[PDB]
Image (tube, coloured by chain):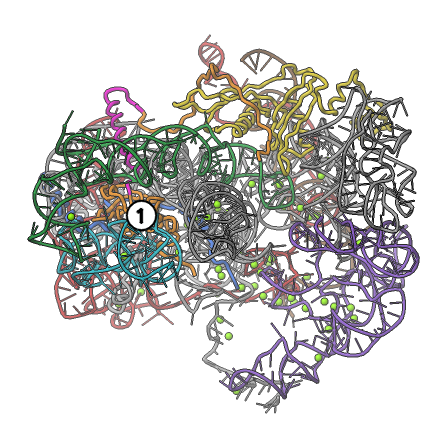
Chain colours: B yellow, C orange, D blue, E green, F purple, G cyan, I red, J brown
Amino acid sequence: GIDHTSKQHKRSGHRTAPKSDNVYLKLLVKLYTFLARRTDAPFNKVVLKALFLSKINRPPVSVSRIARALKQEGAANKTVVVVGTVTDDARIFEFPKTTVAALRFTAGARAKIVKAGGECITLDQLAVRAPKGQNTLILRGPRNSREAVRHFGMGPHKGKAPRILSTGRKFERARGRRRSKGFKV
Amino acid sequence: MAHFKEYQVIGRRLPTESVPEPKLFRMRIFASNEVIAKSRYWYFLQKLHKVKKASGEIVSINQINEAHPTKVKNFGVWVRYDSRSGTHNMYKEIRDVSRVAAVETLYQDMAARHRARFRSIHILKVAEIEKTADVKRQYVKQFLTKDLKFPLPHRVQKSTKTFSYKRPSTFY
Amino acid sequence: GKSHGYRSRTRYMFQRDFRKHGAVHLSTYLKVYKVGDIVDIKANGSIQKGMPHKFYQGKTGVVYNVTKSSVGVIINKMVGNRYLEKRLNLRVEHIKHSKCRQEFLERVKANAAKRAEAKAQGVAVQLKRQPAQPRESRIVSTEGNVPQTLAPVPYETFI
Amino acid sequence: AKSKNHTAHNQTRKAHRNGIKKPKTYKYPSLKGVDPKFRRNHKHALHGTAKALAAAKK
RNA sequence: GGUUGCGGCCAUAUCUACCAGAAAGCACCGUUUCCCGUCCGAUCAACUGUAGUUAAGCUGGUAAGAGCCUGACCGAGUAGUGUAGUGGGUGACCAUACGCGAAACUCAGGUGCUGCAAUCU
RNA sequence: AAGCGUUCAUAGCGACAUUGCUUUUUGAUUCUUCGAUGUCGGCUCUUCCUAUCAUACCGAAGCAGAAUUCGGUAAGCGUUGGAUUGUUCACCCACUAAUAGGGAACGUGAGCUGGGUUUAGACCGUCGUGAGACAGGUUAGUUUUACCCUACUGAUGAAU
RNA sequence: GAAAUCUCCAGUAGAACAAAAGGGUAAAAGCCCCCUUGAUUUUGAUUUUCAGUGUGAAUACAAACCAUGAAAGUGUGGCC
RNA sequence: ACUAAUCGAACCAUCUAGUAGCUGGUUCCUGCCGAAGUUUCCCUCAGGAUAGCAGAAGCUCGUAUCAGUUUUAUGAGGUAAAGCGAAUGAUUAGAGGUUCCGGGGUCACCUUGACCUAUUCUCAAACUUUAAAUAUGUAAGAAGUCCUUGUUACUUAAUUGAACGUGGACAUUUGAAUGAAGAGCUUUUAGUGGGCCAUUUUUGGUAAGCAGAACUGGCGAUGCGGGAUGAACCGAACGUAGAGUUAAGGUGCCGGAAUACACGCUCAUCAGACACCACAAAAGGUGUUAGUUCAUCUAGACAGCCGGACGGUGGCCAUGGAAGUCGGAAUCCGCUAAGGAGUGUGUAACAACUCACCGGCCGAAUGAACUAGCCCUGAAAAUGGAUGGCGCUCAAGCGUGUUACCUAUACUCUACCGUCAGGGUUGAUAUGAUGCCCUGACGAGUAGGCAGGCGUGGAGGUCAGUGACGAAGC
RNA sequence: GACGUAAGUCAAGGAUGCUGGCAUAAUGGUUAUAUGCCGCCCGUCUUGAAACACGGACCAAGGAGUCUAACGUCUAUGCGAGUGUUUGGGUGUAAAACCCAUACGCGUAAUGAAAGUGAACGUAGGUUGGGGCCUCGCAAGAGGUGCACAAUCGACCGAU
RNA sequence: CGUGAAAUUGUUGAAAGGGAAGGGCAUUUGAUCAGACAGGCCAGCAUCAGUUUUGGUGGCA
Ligand SMILES: [Mg+2]
Ligand SMILES: [Mg+2]
Ligand SMILES: [Mg+2]
Ligand SMILES: [Mg+2]
Ligand SMILES: [Mg+2]
Ligand SMILES: [Mg+2]
Ligand SMILES: [Mg+2]
Ligand SMILES: [Mg+2]
Ligand SMILES: [Mg+2]
Ligand SMILES: [Mg+2]
Ligand SMILES: [Mg+2]
Ligand SMILES: [Mg+2]
Ligand SMILES: [Mg+2]
Ligand SMILES: [Mg+2]
Ligand SMILES: [Mg+2]
Ligand SMILES: [Mg+2]
Ligand SMILES: [Mg+2]
Ligand SMILES: [Mg+2]
Ligand SMILES: [Mg+2]
Ligand SMILES: [Mg+2]
Ligand SMILES: [Mg+2]
Ligand SMILES: [Mg+2]
Ligand SMILES: [Mg+2]
Ligand SMILES: [Mg+2]
Ligand SMILES: [Mg+2]
Ligand SMILES: [Mg+2]
Ligand SMILES: [Mg+2]
Ligand SMILES: [Mg+2]
Ligand SMILES: [Mg+2]
Ligand SMILES: [Mg+2]
Ligand SMILES: [Mg+2]
Ligand SMILES: [Mg+2]
Ligand SMILES: [Mg+2]
Ligand SMILES: [Mg+2]
Ligand SMILES: [Mg+2]
Ligand SMILES: [Mg+2]
Ligand SMILES: [Mg+2]
Ligand SMILES: [Mg+2]
Ligand SMILES: [Mg+2]
Ligand SMILES: [Mg+2]
Ligand SMILES: [Mg+2]
Ligand SMILES: [Mg+2]
Ligand SMILES: [Mg+2]
Ligand SMILES: [Mg+2]
Ligand SMILES: [Mg+2]
Ligand SMILES: [Mg+2]
């Protein structure tokens, strides 16, 4: 017998592969597995782990988010890398001429980047031209901005959204939510 | 609690700034080994002085061998022991060749005749009596008679074999 | 039935010390507290306002708020399987500086003094404290100290 | 039909299998419960020093 | 070093009895017009430091003093207590091993120290 | 062992205290049984225990004899017939050597009986407005099955 | 008079503080006198019970308006 | 009561698969993880919600904010103990002083009650001047330390402070030990919300295999070796095997392993061979053993049973009669190496038998009160029976000591299976990259969760699959 | 790594060498039996089941978490500030497949009971961290930039 | 009257049977049965490596 200090036979709790059965994503994982192992560049290990993520773990990255990151000092000429979907954003009116490598582009995002003078490439093209991720800038979309995150941590005084179907008056704006009706939160 | 040895254990309190070089007390301890010897020394030093193993030290451990191991002596052992209902002092008189063998005999004797374990025995003193007729017990005085002789009737002979063909004798 | 009032089971906790009743001396009122100070909580039974609950008797916390005649203290309280941050408003009569912070604040001062002295020469001057070490070997003499001690004493009735 | 009333048996074993956690301190704690007069002035103090570095570092 | 004012710790400072105290200060003391308060200038208020007294207050000393304070290989590593045994004992309980460890008791010593300002043969 | 016992604590007793045993009392518990172990008593029959009533042999006495009392070995052998009561318990008559105490699922209901409790009928007293209540009285009230296995009592029987 | 009013000495609280008990309090938290309404307005924060929900009770504030006092200060009901 | 074998509301059909917090059942395998009977609330107590325990999905990072542990430093507490010539409240006993309602007693009182003063015996869960042990809070640094000066409507008499800052300096001994198995964080949901047992603390109760708490360890949920037997005790927790070594317990035989060695104790006409545990007490015993204290004895001590049983004396009263022995009273020495107003047995009573006290005979140790080991008495229940059984007596019993030996699914080594983790592997990896391979660790499990697979009916595709030369079934 | 001057050898990152018999029931497997030791009847409720708790005489077949509306979390897929062809219409090899307009649902705006109002002082802010990237470095590191995310102080919108 | 299971039964054959029977580990005996000659089966010895056990003897403190 052994006085076990930790739980035995514990899985790491991290994805070692994508749950997706997309054959082309498996080829991207196959390419970046080799790069993460045959290079010491930390960029390849980050990209390989990002290729495993689920859909909510890779939120879309706006072209406006891409353009704001290119306003950083000394970042005006870097290859923006988005392991996920790059969406369009009409609220911006000045996009720069830069190169974006992404897993997926929307039709509007591809049009806006190309029209500005830039170029849209895939992750395998990124690997050929930047094997160690030279002059790259990984961008991640907002993960806690999901609508399900609103209801996480519900409870008194927590200030979270209740899980509700119909909103308005007569739907949870009474006893428990105001001092004139019993108590508040 | 094996074949006993006698130990010359000297210990003292830890010296302080106010009173360095303490009085450096010594005891004679019967114990199976030095680990028990130090433990017994601290135990008896708890009965006498305001000290303990944490606030003191042992400066010397020395085995004491019999000066004349192969001459038969009469020993007077004072002992204080706890019975089931009280503490008693008694005096035993032992005839053997060493203090360790006499003390071993008394531990066997007190366990056999009084059910007093080594746990509840305090060896007050082991002192050889130099002269005959200063001995007080008849069970040892009877062996100090002139030209002592005695037989051993009914000799029991051990047989390696499980069967014997002779129906043997107990002559001696 | 059962009674679980605010000051229940505090018959001896909130007693004053023997021959130490009466008015609180002025030292407690002249001590200056600041945010970040580490303070010990010990309620004064003579002062019934700003008085801590019986749980925080003997607890040590950090000052987060300084007020007119009171001090806000942060205490971590174990509820269930985790600790919870707690915030008390206590008058200065019920708190005092925990002296543990002052020796540590002198050790850091003495550490910097030793390091500054060691800067010019003599590196590795053992800034860290060490536990009590096993004693080194030494010689003990018997000049005036010849060992002499008796055996265990016999059992006397003493009554 | 009488039953057990109360026992803290197994309650410390249960509380320790997930390893009782300290409250995860941070730099810059919440100013909740701090004196409003100090807090009102600290808003004006932080605004001025933010302008001081802005005027100098630029 | 005495004394005064404001203090810190709050009897080593308290309490009882008896003695000393130059100088200064403090004090008792003298007075009732005004401000003020009373049954009562006793207290409280004001006025003159003048008519006086260290008698008291105050301060210090004296006491195999009470109390208090400090320390002790004084009691005592005792009572107690954490841990251990397929230890003892019918049991009540007890012993041992590895640790921690008192109170009363008995002795010895001591009887305020000190901060800021002012003042004094 | 303070006293009683004419004197004498212990022949026989025995205060004030105190140590036990038993599980035939009654309490206390709720572990088993609520897809049910037939809930009182008696009759019948066997066996067991000893804390022995008688009987055998003894020891002690405030044992002269007779009769008694105390104690030992001892459960081998016996311990009854009746009035009243459903009774267990009790009480009385009488005989006797003696009318001792208990256990065995408070032995024993596919052994019986069914007086009692304890369904449904009915009456009384008290209580309740009432329906009804009462370990209060009173009367009437279905007692099933073995042909299996074991056990027991008897009866055959292969193989040597 | 053991005692009805007056006087002095001792008195560490052996009294009193609405109501149980515990704690606390002596130029007071008790007694008497004077003034008074902070037992008021507007919110958040905190403690106990606790799920860190509610209710009750309480704590320190902030922004007002007041009470009292020479003043510092105290006061957001009852010494806790 | 009866109303078609149906009656305290018939029968038939439908609503109706009426509801059920209640009972029963709930169907393949393997792998990994793995509980709770507890918090709060509820017309709640056989239920549910809530928090906790558990699984799964993971996410952000990569050795840290850390820890069912210690040390150092600094707090807190009022239980164990202790105390009552310290407070409160109980409590025993006298002393000394004193004065009033207290004592008949001056008309100032040996033979008094309170009260005071100094002592004395004993106590407290709801007493306390003290006061542990165990447990418990905090701190031991880069979110740190120091220097200089910037903001503010706060604050100060006043940049005096407060808080947050600019700039500069400090480094692996960066500010104790040990460890760290990755660390932190989130979502979601199962089961559970009857508990019970053991040590220690502890309440009610005479007690209980009783009822109720605290901490911990267990059983439940768990097999294995041992306690014959047993949920909980001891030991040790479990993939499939081999070898070795052991734990607890044992080694006469059943039964593996010494009828081993050593010192003693015990003889039971109810021996003993009981950790939990399956019982025995007070009180006793010239049974036997060991010991404590006191006294006597070689100048011949205790006993053995040899001699003397003395003056007043037949001691006073009285007993029908008491003379050494009915009682009251007595107990003086005339004394001797030595004989009492006699230790007893006695007579009407004496008398007489016989002794403490003393020797012409001895010869070595003796006497008393006790202490505790074993054994014995105390010690009585019912079918025949249980140190487990047989049996065991310088033990095969009891106490103690020393070795050797036996064997658990435990430990060590190796193999094989699986799981987890960390890695390697692309210029033909000499084509399986969810593949091949290297390295290390790990494996119990109810309720429950997840994963990988097996099997059945039918459906799309494929094998131009099988088959009257035999399909399916059995 | 060892020995040896070296070649080379070795017990140095896991067994080789030599020899015999048989080549079949010989070893082995399966099965019946015997022997040694062990092994209580499953399921269930339960703190506790072999239980003197309950269901089960046997066998075959049938036999119990399904479907639907709405929804939470997570995952996969398409598109993405949009998304959803299938109410319908067109078409068809005809319940299939293919094509499509306008609406509508949800989302892109909140807040208040409501009347209403309605989201940039700033490089969409400041501070502390933060993977990755860039520059200088043999490296350790230093500096710059710092998405997601965590804490905090602000700013804006609605209510008061 | 397709096939034609099981429970249960008859006959035949085989086996075992002192108050159940059934089962687990291992082997004996009886029965029955699969594959391999271009190494298959069971063994013996020597020299080694790994893990152990049991001795003999040497030199030191
Ligand atoms: Mg209370
Ligand atoms: Mg108040
Ligand atoms: Mg319950
Ligand atoms: Mg005057
Ligand atoms: Mg019960
Ligand atoms: Mg029946
Ligand atoms: Mg008898
Ligand atoms: Mg019966
Ligand atoms: Mg019957
Ligand atoms: Mg019947
Ligand atoms: Mg009847
Ligand atoms: Mg029959
Ligand atoms: Mg019959
Ligand atoms: Mg009807
Ligand atoms: Mg149904
Ligand atoms: Mg129905
Ligand atoms: Mg596990
Ligand atoms: Mg979990
Ligand atoms: Mg207490
Ligand atoms: Mg006590
Ligand atoms: Mg107490
Ligand atoms: Mg339940
Ligand atoms: Mg259960
Ligand atoms: Mg047993
Ligand atoms: Mg067992
Ligand atoms: Mg143990
Ligand atoms: Mg065992
Ligand atoms: Mg044998
Ligand atoms: Mg045996
Ligand atoms: Mg498992
Ligand atoms: Mg079908
Ligand atoms: Mg066929
Ligand atoms: Mg068996
Ligand atoms: Mg049930
Ligand atoms: Mg039950
Ligand atoms: Mg069962
Ligand atoms: Mg049932
Ligand atoms: Mg049945
Ligand atoms: Mg059936
Ligand atoms: Mg079927
Ligand atoms: Mg279609
Ligand atoms: Mg809608
Ligand atoms: Mg047919
Ligand atoms: Mg058949
Ligand atoms: Mg068998
Ligand atoms: Mg065979």
When the figure is inspected, residue C158 is found, relative to residue E90, above or below; the finding is above
Q: Quadrant of residue A14?
A: top left
Residue E73 in the image, given as x and y percentages of width and height: 46, 28
Q: Quadrant of residue D19?
A: top left
Which quadrant, please, contains the C terminus of chain A? bottom left
B152 horizontally vs A27: left or right: right
Residue I12 in the image, given as x and y percentages of width and height: 49, 22
Chain letter of the residue beneath label 1 in the structure image: C
Q: Quadrant of ligand 7?
A: bottom right
When the figure is inspected, residue A81 is found, relative to residue A171, above or below; the finding is above
C50 horizontally vs J14: left or right: left
Does the magenta-highlighted stretch encompass residue C121?
Answer: yes
Does the magenta-highlighted stretch encompass residue C7?
Answer: no
- Give the residue type that dot 1 points to: Asn
> Of F26 and E28, which appears nearest the observer?
E28
Say which element carries label 1.
Answer: loop
What segment is highlighted magenta in the picture?
Answer: C96-125
The answer, for residue C145, to whether it is visible in the render is: yes
Q: Residue at x 53, y 19 (%)?
A: C148
When the figure is inspected, residue C91 is found, relative to residue I112, above or below; the finding is above
Q: Quadrant of residue B112?
A: top right
Residue holding disc 1: C44
> Of G74 and D42, which appears nearest the observer?
G74
> Of B42 and B85, which appears nearest the observer?
B85
The dominant secondary structure in magenta is helix
The answer, for residue A28, to whether it is visible in the render is: no
